[PDB]
Image: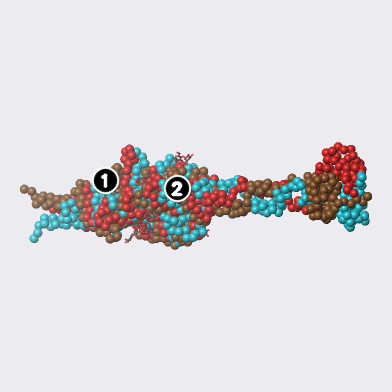
Chain colours: A red, B cyan, C brown
Amino acid sequence: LRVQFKRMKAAEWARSDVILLESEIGFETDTGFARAGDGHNRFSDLGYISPLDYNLLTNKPNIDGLATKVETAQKLQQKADKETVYTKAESKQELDKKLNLKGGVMTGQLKFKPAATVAYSSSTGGAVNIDLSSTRGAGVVVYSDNDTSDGPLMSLRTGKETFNQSALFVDYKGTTNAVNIAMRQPTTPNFSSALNITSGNENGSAMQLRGSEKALGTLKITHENPSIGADYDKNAAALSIDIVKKTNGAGTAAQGIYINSTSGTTGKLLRIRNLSDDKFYVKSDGGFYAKETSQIDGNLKLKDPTANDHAATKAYVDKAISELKKLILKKH
Amino acid sequence: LRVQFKRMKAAEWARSDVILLESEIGFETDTGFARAGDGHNRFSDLGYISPLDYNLLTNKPNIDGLATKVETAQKLQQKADKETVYTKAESKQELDKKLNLKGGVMTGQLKFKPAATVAYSSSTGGAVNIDLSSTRGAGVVVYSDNDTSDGPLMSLRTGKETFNQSALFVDYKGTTNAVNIAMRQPTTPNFSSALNITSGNENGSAMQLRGSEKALGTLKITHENPSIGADYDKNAAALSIDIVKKTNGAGTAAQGIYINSTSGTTGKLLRIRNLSDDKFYVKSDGGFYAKETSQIDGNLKLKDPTANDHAATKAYVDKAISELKKLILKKH
Amino acid sequence: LRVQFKRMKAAEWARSDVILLESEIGFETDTGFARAGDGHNRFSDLGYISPLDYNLLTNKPNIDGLATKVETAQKLQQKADKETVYTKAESKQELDKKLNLKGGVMTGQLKFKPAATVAYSSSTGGAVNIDLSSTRGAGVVVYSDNDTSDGPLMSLRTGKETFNQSALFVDYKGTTNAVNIAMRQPTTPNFSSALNITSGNENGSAMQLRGSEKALGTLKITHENPSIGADYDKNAAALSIDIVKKTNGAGTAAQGIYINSTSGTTGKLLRIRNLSDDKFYVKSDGGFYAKETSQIDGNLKLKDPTANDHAATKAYVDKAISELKKLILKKH
Ligand SMILES: OC[C@H]1O[C@@H](O[C@H]2[C@H](O)[C@@H](O)[C@@H](O)O[C@@H]2CO)[C@H](O)[C@@H](O)[C@H]1O
Ligand SMILES: OC[C@H]1O[C@@H](O[C@H]2[C@H](O)[C@@H](O)[C@@H](O)O[C@@H]2CO)[C@H](O)[C@@H](O)[C@H]1O
Ligand SMILES: OC[C@H]1O[C@@H](O[C@H]2[C@H](O)[C@@H](O)[C@@H](O)O[C@@H]2CO)[C@H](O)[C@@H](O)[C@H]1O
Ligand SMILES: OC[C@H]1O[C@@H](O[C@H]2[C@H](O)[C@@H](O)[C@@H](O)O[C@@H]2CO)[C@H](O)[C@@H](O)[C@H]1O
Ligand SMILES: OC[C@H]1O[C@@H](O[C@H]2[C@H](O)[C@@H](O)[C@@H](O)O[C@@H]2CO)[C@H](O)[C@@H](O)[C@H]1O
Ligand SMILES: OC[C@H]1O[C@@H](O[C@H]2[C@H](O)[C@@H](O)[C@@H](O)O[C@@H]2CO)[C@H](O)[C@@H](O)[C@H]1O
Ligand SMILES: OC[C@H]1O[C@@H](O[C@H]2[C@H](O)[C@@H](O)[C@@H](O)O[C@@H]2CO)[C@H](O)[C@@H](O)[C@H]1O
Ligand SMILES: OC[C@H]1O[C@@H](O[C@H]2[C@H](O)[C@@H](O)[C@@H](O)O[C@@H]2CO)[C@H](O)[C@@H](O)[C@H]1O
Ligand SMILES: OC[C@H]1O[C@@H](O[C@H]2[C@H](O)[C@@H](O)[C@@H](O)O[C@@H]2CO)[C@H](O)[C@@H](O)[C@H]1O
């Protein structure tokens, strides 16, 4: 037996009306495939003589180990996209432009414009609040070594006439000077001043000073000769006063120096000394003393003498002469 | 020949004891599948007559191109999760709340509380350190155009009596005034002062001033009439002094003006002029000069005259009279 | 019929020259596989009698649902890597080191070194610019409650002699004192001063003051007795002046107090009172008044008397005596 089977091309079977007997094999000549009869179905309705089911295969690949598009996408959706997020480098680049609380260097202007909760009161208020209670350094240190400039080191301005606080308030306890102004010996000379004050206020002193010294002056002024030359400073003074009219005024009636004691003092109201020796003084009652010969380009009105060293008046002289003239003419 | 084969249902083969001859075909009537004999195995132990090995298939899918769960997970593990990381927008939102070193606007309080390395000394110390050496602007510019307020523009306070530094130190070189206080002509008038100083310190002057002017006063004061009216300021003064007791004190012995030269000066100790003409002065030795008629409501003690223009004393008058009385009575 | 087929091992077929007839089955005894003849090809060139094409299988897996390495990699490439990006925690850790514009606490030094656009001029310049126009708090509040320190609360320094701005400028409008210095009654006593000024400048006053008061002094000084003891302050003064030579100088010619009116005043140039009663004064023309007995340790040069209360001169006395001597001797 060399057995051969009913056979033709797949497409010819496809339209054959031949019914294979149950288990009778038929052959597709162009595919090599067989199919077996069931006794009723046409060829195209028979299945192949061997399984075609993925689940019966051997050497299957690991389908279950492979990632699904859905599950991968869900996992990607939790991850941050490059474009919506700064790198470490761009983060640091941005942060290096900001000021550390530990400290840093400003190259531009720091403005304050408080919104003002209340901005407090005392040692806990202010837009800038500096507490040096636990440290030995300075608070605010401003300086310039520039040759010239357009602005002061520090400027304080108030714009409204009702303003009811000070520009600068110094409340000081300690053992040196609350406020100290040193104007160092000039090389190129200024025609100006350590401290300069002008007021146009007619209802208040330009400067007020109250002190309560046991044995010093409330204000102490010392002039020191700038030169070793004994008389170089001959036009200088410890205190100089001028009294002037208003530009285009008719003049002035202001006094130079006015001294009073509202409670009454027993001290000398004006005491002038040289080398610590009294030279001239006005006592608390208005009597004066002068150490040396003095001059008046005028007369002197005073009372009649009662002691030998009293200056005589014209009355006293005239009377003593008139007495002598009478007696001497003789008396009956 | 129409060949048919030993046949029955798969499940019936499954328990048949029939041994197919080597290569003899048997048919599963309900599956369509054949199996071929090996001459020993029961039907259920024969394999199908055609391969069932994934590796022999054609049109395989690209299994190797597909991603594995393991390898995807490893790759996801290097990526940043959305939730642990700021977006660019939230980054910028946070950074815009911080101050740029280039500059910016504070809306709240900046406090300093130095921890203090040493906080240095001189032109490199301070919690706030401003160096204007290479620029032409101002250092610290504080101002207010508010009508009223509860606090000063600037406040300096020291709390302990041992405190051994100044509240404010000005070390100045330059060509204008180190410190300048302008109190602008008021519209609504203050009863106060450009500069006001009080000290309760009995061992130190409230204010100390030293200068070394060639031809000016160490302190120069000018009063200017506030009005064009010649005598409007008739109660005004360039300098006014008061001398008062302590509240509930018995009084005071303090002097008004005390002038000394500890090294000895040849200048006039008190010089009073009007329109630049000497009117009254006290010389370095205590002699005074007065330009016009003067009055004492009292006597004047002085020495006996020796020149024609010297004031005479009662002694001198009495003696000259007593001489004339004698001579004239005549002498034996 | 029990049909058997041409058969041998796969490897033996592999080199057989037997040609199966068209559809004649041949069997591989070691694999179980059949192949069918085409009438020309050797065994090894026939295909199996049943399909081996993945596309004809049933129960296929969802290959299309699975993610490709390429497509996953493209998706991963858009995601940010953990290592190149800050977590929220490290972001906040960095940001907490920076200063909020809302406010914050500096623990280190804030330096300014302006690059200077121009740094402006007026109420819009300065490295630190504080505008309190809409608020009621203080501007700059510096204080210390430390026992001692190495630096001042505030320090202003200019290094070059040409410097042509002020260290401190106060431009004040308002109703209290522009600048106020309180030196609180000491418990441990300082030998120093509320305000201390030194100048080595020979071409400018150490301090300049101009005021235009209707009825006050430009400078007002009050000394108050520190004690209830009436004469405790007997060495004190409201104003004290000293006039000294330069260290290693030959001396000085400086004046003590110099008073002038450059425009001419009709006021009293020096007025001394006690309990508000005139005790001594120098009029605008140089005439003086003294309330009580006075003394000169010297002579007084003055003009010849013309009124009864005028002091007499030696000339006047000598002449009146010489007249009496003549008349009395009698006249022919
Ligand atoms: O910071 C600017 C404010 O200026 C205020 O106006 C006055 C100021 O009060 C006065 O002293 C002087 O400086 O002139 C100013 C106007 O030129 C304004 O009223 C206020 O609105 C601000 O512009
Ligand atoms: O006070 C404001 C102005 O002060 C001027 O200085 C003048 C001063 O006003 C004047 O009275 C006299 O003493 O000369 C002073 C110069 O030493 C400033 O020059 C000017 O800028 C204003 O700030
Ligand atoms: O510029 C004011 C200074 O004037 C000096 O007075 C000169 C005065 O100008 C001159 O006429 C002459 O009399 O010598 C005076 C000094 O002895 C003041 O001395 C000086 O202190 C300034 O006030
Ligand atoms: O910043 C507050 C500090 O105050 C210090 O106490 C004193 C201060 O020295 C004195 O001058 C006055 O201001 O009274 C204060 C107490 O009420 C404290 O000693 C210090 O602990 C701080 O609280
Ligand atoms: O010095 C601290 C206080 O100064 C007061 O001003 C007074 C001053 O004390 C007084 O002696 C007199 O001259 O009147 C001044 C007002 O012009 C302030 O009023 C007060 O707030 C304290 O700061
Ligand atoms: O408030 C102090 C001022 O007193 C003025 O003195 C007046 C004085 O009060 C009055 O009794 C009368 O004698 O006129 C005086 C002025 O001529 C001072 O003149 C003034 O400078 C202030 O000290
Ligand atoms: O901030 C330091 C600058 O100091 C300037 O030099 C002078 C200064 O002008 C003078 O007043 C005194 O302080 O001595 C200094 C030099 O020791 C320098 O010229 C400048 O280059 C800076 O170093
Ligand atoms: O002005 C700079 C210095 O002031 C000194 O204080 C001295 C002052 O100079 C002197 O003339 C006299 O009045 O004694 C003062 C002390 O009360 C400071 O001591 C010194 O640190 C310098 O800053
Ligand atoms: O240290 C300067 C103070 O001197 C006081 O003068 C004393 C003086 O030293 C003494 O010789 C004696 O005459 O008593 C004087 C006071 O009556 C000043 O009184 C004082 O104001 C300071 O200048």
Label 1: element kind:
loop
Mark 1 beta carbon near ligand 3 (under 8 Å): yes
Labels 2 & 1 near each other (Cβ < 8 A): no
Q: Is residue B74 in view?
A: yes
Q: Which of C164 and A256 is in front in this view?
A: C164
The 10 Å Cα crowd at callout 2, few under 14, some 14 to 19, many 20 or more, is: some
Q: Find residue A330 and name its label.
A: none
Q: Find residue C115 and name its label.
A: 2
Q: Residue furthest left?
A: C332
Q: Name the residue under label 1.
A: B276
**What residue do we see at 79% from left, 50% from top?**
C44
Q: Position of residue C274 (x, y in %)?
A: 35, 52
Give the residue type that dot 2 points to.
Answer: Ala
Give the residue type that dot 1 points to.
Answer: Ser
Q: How far apart are marks 2 and 1 (CA)?
A: 52 Å
Residue A14 as seen in the image, left or right of residue C99 = right
**What residue do we see at 83% from left, 42% from top?**
A29
**What residue do we see at 23% from left, 58% from top?**
C297
Q: Position of residue C106 (x, y in %)?
A: 52, 54
Q: In this view, does A254 lie above or below C232?
A: above
Residue C180 as seen in the image, left or right of residue B59 = left
Residue B25 as seen in the image, left or right of residue C88 = right
